[PDB]
Amino acid sequence: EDLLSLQEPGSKTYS
Amino acid sequence: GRVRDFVAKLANNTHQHVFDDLRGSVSLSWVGDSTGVILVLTTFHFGQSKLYRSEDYGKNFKDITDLINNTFIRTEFGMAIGPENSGKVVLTAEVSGGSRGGRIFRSSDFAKNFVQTDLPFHPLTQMMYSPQNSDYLLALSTENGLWVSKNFGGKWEEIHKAVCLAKWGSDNTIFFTTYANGSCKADLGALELWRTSDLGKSFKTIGVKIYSFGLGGRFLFASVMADKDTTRRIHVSTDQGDTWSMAQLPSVGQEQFYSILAANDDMVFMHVDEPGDTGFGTIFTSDDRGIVYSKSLDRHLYTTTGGETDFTNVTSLRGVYITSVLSEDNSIQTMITFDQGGRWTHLRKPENSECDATAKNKNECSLHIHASYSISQKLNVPMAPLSEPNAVGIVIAHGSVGDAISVMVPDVYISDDGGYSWTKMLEGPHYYTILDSGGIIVAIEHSSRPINVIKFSTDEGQCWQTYTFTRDPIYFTGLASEPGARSMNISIWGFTESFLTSQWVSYTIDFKDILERNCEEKDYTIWLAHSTDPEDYEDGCILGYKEQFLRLRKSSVCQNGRDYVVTKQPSICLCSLEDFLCDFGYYRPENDSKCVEQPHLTTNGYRKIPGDKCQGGVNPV
Ligand SMILES: *[C@@H]1O[C@H](CO)[C@@H](O[C@@H]2O[C@H](CO)[C@@H](O)[C@H](O)[C@H]2NC(C)=O)[C@H](O)[C@H]1NC(C)=O
Ligand SMILES: *[C@@H]1O[C@H](CO)[C@@H](O[C@@H]2O[C@H](CO)[C@@H](O)[C@H](O)[C@H]2NC(C)=O)[C@H](O)[C@H]1NC(C)=O
Ligand SMILES: *[C@@H]1O[C@H](CO)[C@@H](O)[C@H](O)[C@H]1NC(C)=O
């Protein structure tokens, strides 16, 4: 696949 | 240099909250800005969830789990926070085996009250908001249908049945791809691209034989398979797909890929993997049209199709980027560019550090920075480089000095003029953060044992002081703060040492009494950016113009405030032959700067580099 779109961040996660 | 009597001031402003629940996982989301609403979604495994809401920047939390009526929530999708200041939150629950459709709890008042609805389908992807109007949503069901809602989830309508991928464009326009025979996997390279400006009332076909597509700002990219081979080129359109024009990029094979590293309104950075699994590629930079591409860097680092790269846009200073290259011996190295990709060089060596074993010449080495790749290899790199647009010319990151990125424990280095000069700030890995637009910095040690101390500096990482915030040390887990780097509250998470039964905990510290005074006219100095040689008639003129900021002095201890906005004063510079790039049918001969001809639309002469604002002087058509 080709990454032709910027991937914005998600959510802070911990554990 | 230190201020005194800060211990009591920090002691009064410290708040502890302890969550009574099983230790599973946590998720933190900020709803809007200037509201201080924080939603914490605790989950455990079977299915069981708890929801907490804080209206006070995280100093106190309330248990609103009964609002969602104690139902397990799917954390794979995550919370869908609405765009800008609208306070729209949507959650996705888990349903039984005989359910007709999924179920969502939706709120539109910053999670004060939630409403339960039953969908006609089973959403297989997170809900997406229309940027121009938050009342619109779309999602893909398990059967690959496309459902669009025009009243914020009240009702949905199916507008197609074989959609591979979809995403909002601009002005409430939807782009999606469809397949005919077989699944979306076996039919790759033989898809169609569809557009509809009426929310699925009227459709249109804008492409065929598509391999993938994406949006990169004011550009539309689509990778089209060749008619007789497996090679696929790149087609770019800026008219919502009304008309396409081939881009001047190499046609990659079936074992390679493209990747957009950063896309502005004018320039786009493209990465083209080289044939083979050598592990490196190349970078090209476009022009204002997004069609003509010129080679910028070689042997760029990119692990794999789904891998990671070290490319980083330094937001503090204009036109500064950092990335990692690959040497002849597979020894990674760091390069920096100040001309938006015009030239690349090594990071300047710190003036008061000694080269490590990796450097053969003990009087000649350079600084190297750890990034996503180093974290991937499981090294001691708690964080990647940090920088904020509103904090001018400040960069923080781990790094080591030598001829290649080493494997020893890294230190922390800071630059306060955009990246031209560096200096060691702390020793050993740390978690750092910036508050109040660079007014005060904070850092937490990265250790394998409980910690009960936090460091902070007011002179841009020059003088550090330690504050003991808790009597019972906790295992640190991470820092949290309001996005934008304009607040003064900082939240410190972790979990207590209790061996029989551990628990979560958060400490929030407010620095309102450390920065007692508000900055005045006197507490600002005029600073010229990109300054290298004062003798130059146009010293520090990048892309045709300069900029003179007003920056808070390090000595001045004062608060910028939430309404602070940076000040500037650009002045243009005369154009030269170095402000233009080549067109379709021309190239640059080596050792020269002219653009000669190489041995359908037509071009005459040169083209002006995007982002360049010079005027006057040389103008070769
Ligand atoms: C690199 O980051 C900088 C800082 O965030 C970006 O500069 C902003 O670009 C946007 C989009 O055009 C403008 O609206 C802002 O005014 C810019 N802010 C500045 C210059 O302080 C820049 O676009 C990023 N570069 C790329 C190539 O994406
Ligand atoms: C840090 O958190 C405090 C609350 O703990 C924020 O206080 C708000 O300040 C604004 C601006 O004066 C008031 O209108 C709000 O009423 C305050 N909130 C509350 C809940 O009383 C404070 O603003 C935060 N830090 C910064 C820099 O804004
Ligand atoms: C809350 O969930 C319970 C689970 O047993 C269900 O029976 C009940 O109808 C739900 N209440 C509302 C108001 O939807």
Image (cartoon, coloured by chain):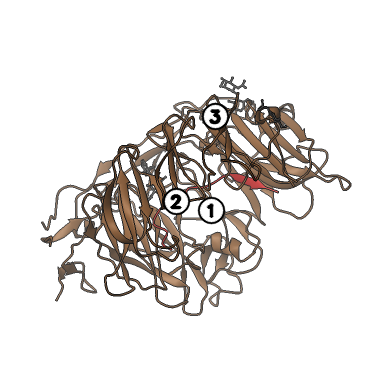
Chain colours: A red, B brown
- Secondary structure of the residue carrying tag 2 is loop
Q: Assess mark 2: CB under 8 A from ligand 1?
A: yes
Front position in the image: B484 or B17? B17
Query: Is residue B295 rendered to the left or right of residue B345?
Result: left
What residue is at 68 percent from the left and 34 percent from the top? B51
Residue B559 got which mark?
Answer: 3
Q: Is residue B426 above or below residue B470?
A: below
Circles 1, 2 touching at the beta carbon (< 8 Å): yes
Q: Chain of mark 2?
A: B
Q: Quadrant of ligand 3?
A: top right
Residue type at mark 3 is Gln
Front position in the image: B326 or B404? B326
Q: Position of residue B19 (x, y in %)?
A: 76, 35
Q: Earlier in the sequence, mark 3 or mark 1?
A: 1
Q: Position of residue B53 (x, y in %)?
A: 65, 30
Q: Earlier in the sequence, mark 1 or mark 2?
A: 2
Query: Is residue B585 rendered to the left or right of residue B526?
Result: left
Front position in the image: B258 or B486? B258
Residue B317 in sight in this render: yes
Measure how far apart labels 3 and 1 are at the Cα level: 25 Å
Neighbourhood count class around disc 1 (C-alpha, 10 Å): few under 14, some 14–19, many 20 upward: many
Residue type at mark 1 is Pro
Circles 2, 3 touching at the beta carbon (< 8 Å): no
Q: Is residue B226 above or below residue B413?
A: below
Quadrant containing the C terminus of chain B is: bottom left
Q: Earlier in the sequence, mark 2 or mark 3?
A: 2
Q: Assess mark 3: CB under 8 A from ligand 2?
A: yes
Residue type at mark 2 is Val
